[PDB]
Length: 294
Length: 294
Length: 21
Length: 21
Ligand SMILES: [Mn+2]
Ligand SMILES: [Mn+2]
Image 1 (cartoon, helix red, strand yellow):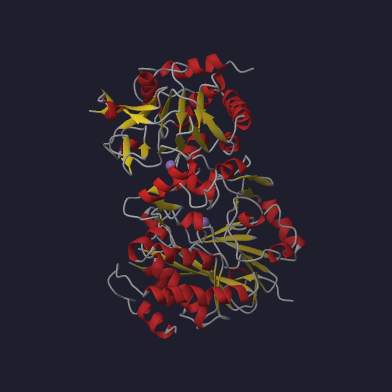
Image 2: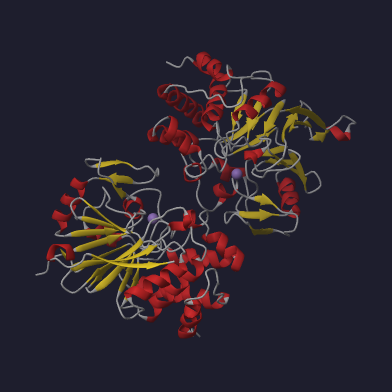
């Protein structure tokens, strides 16, 4: 069984507590959340097609109490429809509570809650940057492998009313038609190069005229003329993405044709940045909601 | 062309100098090192078959000065044949001088100098643990990708006089016959799992009767029983490996049926360990030569 | 079909600030 | 025809030590 109300309740019960109180669910409950949510991810299309109104968040990176502050201001599900753009674990202390509360809502409201895959929702990355460590200390190694099998079926991109294109990373030189995105057959591992790798790793750059090499050593960088031609060929108007920490929680690119979202404020304590989320009304009009520390 | 003597000369020029003095070879000199050694690596069998006497080293990890100290004691090539178990880059301040002097000697005496592939000779690892950062700083990204295409061709294991089996990591559950090692065609990436992954990632553990899950989240731990049954099946007397820092640079296991080597003393400054290398003469008798800080 | 718009184009404030500690 | 042996087996010194700083 999955007493999900008891799970979501025991997670939200620490709301307002002193910072630093963990939520240790049972190994078989967390194991059940992965299987029941993986069941959902594979049933839904790999290229999600969503309808507004919808609230879009960026990266979380294990800042669970900061994920809760996002929900009180944005409305706890099912108040507003939600779509996340990956990067839920790592670089933060509470990665397990973060992904569990996100996996919990995805099961409770499977048509009003949505999660995309990020480059940190991959085995070879979260092993190093602190998520697998969080599994080792509080649970066992096999649970982290259960988490990997769940991430290996997350959707990659989401198209909101054929005018907003959402993904964690950015554009891909090998991306010519949406059928290439649907042609990807889950479960999948994120490769080191190619179409699937680029959608989770590429960055925008104002200095590149075309496709340039990325500093991360993975994927490429695209310029303002790449975004404009892409929106033009697929009758799109906006590219929403994350994958890059921004000072104001939001950062525009290519004359507002693209925007970078980062939802984790005070990211891992080495920046003083703020976290923002993008709200979308019925008329595809967008408003930014920002969390700023003082 | 390849002024190989000049390259070795400028690399050995910092012998006895103050710690931290680099050797900046030109991009074309280094690119020539990777391309000519990769030619040698692909010609020599992926499973090396060497003859004693020779001296085996473990992990250097970019400790270039410490590598020079190892060459001082054991003799500079070609005074003694050398076998290295991998992990030349990463964690060290001078990964470039380390790998360059190693690949240069590999071209200079390819029949008396040998290099095996470690788990850090992979694009997914050295991109994170300092080597790729060291390539961006002193050179360009393209050199790092040229280094990767050379590491993908390093040989995996060696058998010395049909009695000493040598690899970086350790045994593998899938490893049944030596033809399976030779079957692997180069170049390849260090895969996510399997025979090649374990040969570069597995460790020996005393508390495991058989195969158990590894702490790193990659590969397995094997026990003293697995060592004995493996040696008995292939008529081998000793397994020589590295991949793990040990206090005295050398460490026995399973009643001297396996030895762990680590050649980098004061491992990146966070350990008070020592560095050692194993000397095998023509009688297949083993001596240890240790470097220790005071 | 509906096209994307922004709050600053229609006079609405684009940014809504919330602070914590 | 051959067999692996060790210096400690024959009474020789197994380890050769060098110091530096
Ligand atoms: Mn990212
Ligand atoms: Mn290693």
